[PDB]
Image: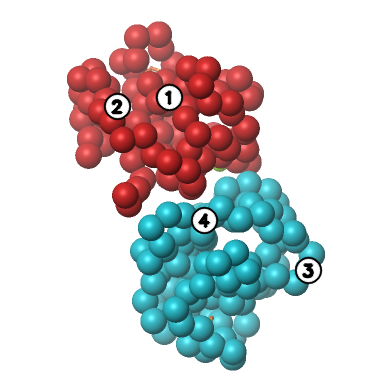
Chain colours: A cyan, B red
Amino acid sequence: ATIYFSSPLMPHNKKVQAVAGKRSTLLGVAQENGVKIPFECQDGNCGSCLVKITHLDGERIKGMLLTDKERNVLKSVGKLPRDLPPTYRLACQTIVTDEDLLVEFTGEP
Amino acid sequence: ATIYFSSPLMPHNKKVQAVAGKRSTLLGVAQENGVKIPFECQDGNCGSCLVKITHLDGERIKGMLLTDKERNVLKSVGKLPRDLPPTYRLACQTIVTDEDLLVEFTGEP
Ligand code: FES
Ligand code: FES
Ligand SMILES: [Mg+2]
Ligand SMILES: [Mg+2]
């Protein structure tokens, strides 16, 4: 999958080729490619990795992808929701698939 | 350049690899890859090819890209305007460069 990372904190977007099937996350791939957001956490509760995801190409994975915790974090920042509109996720919880994506970090802590 | 075409009239987006430097347009590349919008014109006045363009990667070409005619067509549909926000263009007037793009047709005649 090809992922384009964007952030108010990045002067340029970063285009990354990611191998699906190795249990990678959007945040892990970003850091692995030198896209190191300033704040993160180990329990998926901080919300700092919030991203707006735009579908570019490939199959979307039809399935319940949000744990109760991620849903509660998204609700607490006002972002709880075959056409594919932009969707909000915690990047540290978002599993990389074969889908090509535009991934926009919000930049707030 | 990689271009992702999207339209309310397309069930799936279409990812295209385009060679820059051969005086290609977004509409020409789309048709060349089987993305044939239903309506078009030869004088760039019909407005049917209106697209919303999102920057994905690569250098943006800094230069006056809009003729008076395209500006007037864009104004007539309410779409006249190193950070790169989404911009509206006539796809038949938009020259392909090395920039990777998401290109969304509006779908209206
Ligand atoms: S890095 Fe803390 S919620 Fe994702
Ligand atoms: S195809 Fe008519 S203005 Fe572009
Ligand atoms: Mg940026
Ligand atoms: Mg579509």
Mark 2 or mark 4: which is in front?
4
Q: Which residue is mark 4?
A: A14
Relative to B46, does residue B56 appear above or below in the rendering?
below
Q: Chain of mark 1?
A: B
Q: Callout 3, which amino acid?
A: Lys
Q: Residue at x 33, y 40 (%)?
A: B87
- What label sits on residue B95 in the rendered view? 1
Label 4: state its secondary structure.
strand
Q: Callout 1, which amino acid?
A: Ile
Q: How packed is label 2: few (under 14 Cα within 10 Å), some, or many (20 or more)? A: few
Q: How packed is label 1: few (under 14 Cα within 10 Å), some, or many (20 or more)? A: some
Q: Which residue is mark 2?
A: B65
Q: Which residue is mark 3?
A: A22
Q: Are marks 3 and 1 in contact (CB under 8 Å)?
A: no
Q: Are marks 1 and 2 on the same chain?
A: yes
Q: As rendered, which of A54 and B96 lies closer to the eye? A: B96
Relative to B81, does residue A103 appear above or below in the rendering?
below
Quarter of image, ligand 4: top right
* Residue B92 place in picture, x, y as percent: 42, 20
Q: How packed is label 3: few (under 14 Cα within 10 Å), some, or many (20 or more)? A: few
C-alpha gap between disc 2 and disc 4: 25 Å
Left or right relative to A80: residue A22: right
C-alpha gap between disc 2 and disc 3: 43 Å
Mark 4 or mark 1: which is in front?
4
Left or right relative to B92: residue B78: left
Q: Are marks 2 and 3 in contact (CB under 8 Å)?
A: no
* Residue A77 place in picture, x, y as percent: 40, 80
